[PDB]
Length: 74
Image (cartoon, rainbow, N blue to C red; front, side):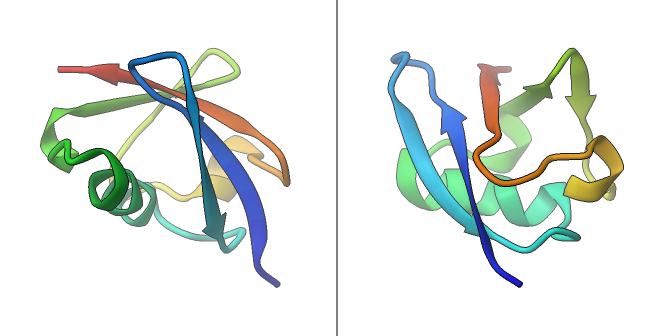
C-alpha cells in the first residue's frame, strides 16, 4: 500500500517521504520534523492550491504517488 511523495522544503530542495494513502497530515508533518527539524506547529503545507490541515488525511486532497507538497514556515 505504501507510496512515495515529496516535500519541497524552505531551501527549494525536496525531501522524499514514504507514506500511506490515508495518512493524516499530522504524520506527514512529523516526518518533515524528523528530517528538517521544524516543529509541526511551525509548518504550513500546500498542495495544488490547498492548505493541508491537521486532522485531515492525504486522501482528502487527492495526494497520489510522486506528489510534491510545498512547505511554508510559520
